[PDB]
Length: 37
Length: 49
Image: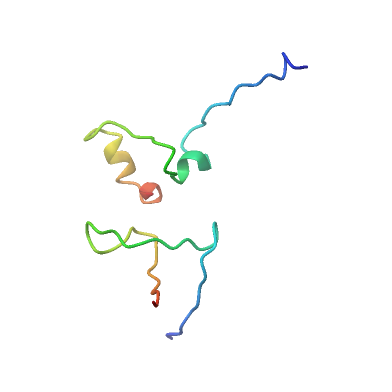
């Protein structure tokens, strides 16, 4: 099934980073996480 | 005690320590472009960072 998951930004637990600009997709073993502004 | 325990700033172990496993801006480690080291880290999926 599909469900929404919320996540904050902590140091070793969940590290957010911008997507790779050279390809538009980030590295492997790094799941996407939308951010609202 | 001072002379015996006057340790240096230590050194770096193999590719396992957090000092090297996850990068930092101050730290700079690199190898020679287009070599076996290049296609050892690129091939591995854990060593992508």
